[PDB]
């Protein structure tokens, strides 16, 4: 059981609001028309709210609900990208992204805009009530880079071209939208980091390490369903192509890279410089937030129907 090798020298927590938030995320999905024909009794088992509850365990219920609805949005968008025709059609993906980008700039959806565009506009509206412009611009840019990454995946599928390890790992940091999920830690923890701390090389490196761990963990758990769809956006499949090795060996190599990235994250935690008492207090809440996300991703994914 190679899954038992997905271990961390720390553990997570879950918000006491978990089930309330999950029920509300389903009601939200139904309200905005995101639940497709194939899903009726499968809808109950999505449990997207129970991932959010683990990722932001200390958040107030209102802020947690924005995070849960956002996480659900990302799953709904992802299944369109990864399991339908739109992920093989760059021109259809560009037309959709043009609508999302107009909504991220604060435009109102038109009558004939799709459910995902309306739902994205709802999340932006609710975030604008809770966050300053500075934060909203950083979130929006992280979301734009997720769309760019999805268009990158679409070109790979159209060309039938598996990326090399260096290209894949560099792009995978954007294709999972993990940086946009990290932005929400600030709102969950109600912390205001000054510019020089927010963008410090050690903070960027801790964010990169946490993002890598989360994505490579997902890759080990999601290679089966991704292979079932003839997809190629997975460290296991990418390693297999580069090394011309067996699937068991590629899995072994992916888990080695995961273990190494956990150690890098633990090491770099002890390298955060002393700015001042108030800045380092806030900074340690953010970095603790990254740990909660690492654990949430693993803890939710091992039990989720999504990877069963
Ligand atoms: C692999 C991912 C890890 C981060 C988990 C979380 C952000 C889920 C939503 C988002 C889309 C792609 C589901 C992310 C993917
Ligand atoms: Mg995807
Ligand atoms: Mg996917
Ligand atoms: Mg995956």
Image: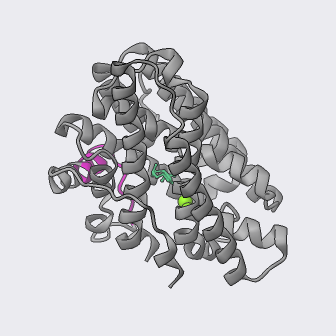
Asked which quadrant contains residue 12, the reply is: bottom left
Residue shown at 81%/58% (left/top)?
Answer: 164
User: Does residue 34 appear left or right of residue 199 in this picture?
Assistant: left
Magenta extent: 25-37
Q: Is residue 134 magenta?
A: no
Q: Is residue 299 above or below residue 152?
A: below
Horizontal and vertical percent position of residue 33: 34, 48
Residue shown at 56%/27% (left/top)?
Answer: 141
Horizontal and vertical percent position of residue 289: 37, 42
Total of numbered circles in the picture?
Answer: 0
Horizontal and vertical percent position of residue 93: 64, 43
User: Does residue 261 appear left or right of residue 68 in this picture?
Assistant: right
Residue shown at 18%/39% (left/top)?
Answer: 61
Q: Is residue 227 above or below residue 34?
A: below
Q: Is residue 32 above or below residue 285?
A: below
Horizontal and vertical percent position of residue 27: 22, 50
Residue shown at 44%/21% (left/top)?
Answer: 136
Which color scheme did the rendering employ for the protein?
A: one colour
Between 132 and 201, the residue placed more toward the observer is 201
Q: Assign the C terminus to one quadrant of the image.
A: bottom left
């Amino acid at each position: 059981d190679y899954r038992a090798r997905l271990v961390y020298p720390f553990s997570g927590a879950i918000s006491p609001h978990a089930d309330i938030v999950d029920q509300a995320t389903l009601a939200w999905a139904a309200m905005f028309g995101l639940l497709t024909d194939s899903l009726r009794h499968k809808s109950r088992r999505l449990q997207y709210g129970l991932l959010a509850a683990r990722a932001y365990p200390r958040a107030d219920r209102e802020m947690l609900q924005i995070a849960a609805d956002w996480i659900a949005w990302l799953f709904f968008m992802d299944d369109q990208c990864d399991e339908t025709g739109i992920g093989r059609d760059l021109q259809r993906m560009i037309a959709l992204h043009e609508r999302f980008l107009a909504i991220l700039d604060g435009a109102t959806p038109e009558a004939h805009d799709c459910a995902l565009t309306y739902a994205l506009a709802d999340l932006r509206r609710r975030l604008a009530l809770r966050a300053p412009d500075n934060w909203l611009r950083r979130f929006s840019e992280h979301v734009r880079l997720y769309f760019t990454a999805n268009r990158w995946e679409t070109v790979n599928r159209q060309r039938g071209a598996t990326p090399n390890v260096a290209t894949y790992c560099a792009a995978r940091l954007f294709s999972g939208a993990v940086y946009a999920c990290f932005d929400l830690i600030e709102l969950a923890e109600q912390i205001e980091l000054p510019f020089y701390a927010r963008h410090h090389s050690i903070v960027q490196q801790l964010e990169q390490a946490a993002n890598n761990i989360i994505c490579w963990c997902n890759d080990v758990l999601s290679y089966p369903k991704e292979m079932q769809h003839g997809d190629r956006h997975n460290l296991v499949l990418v390693i297999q192509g580069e090394h011309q090795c067996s699937l068991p060996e590629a899995i072994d190599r992916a888990l080695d890279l995961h273990a190494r990235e956990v150690a890098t994250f633990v090491r770099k935690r002890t390298c955060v410089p002393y700015f001042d008492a108030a800045v380092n207090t806030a900074l340690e809440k953010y970095v603790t937030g990254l740990q909660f996300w690492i654990c949430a991703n693993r803890d939710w994914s091992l039990t989720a129907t999504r990877y069963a």
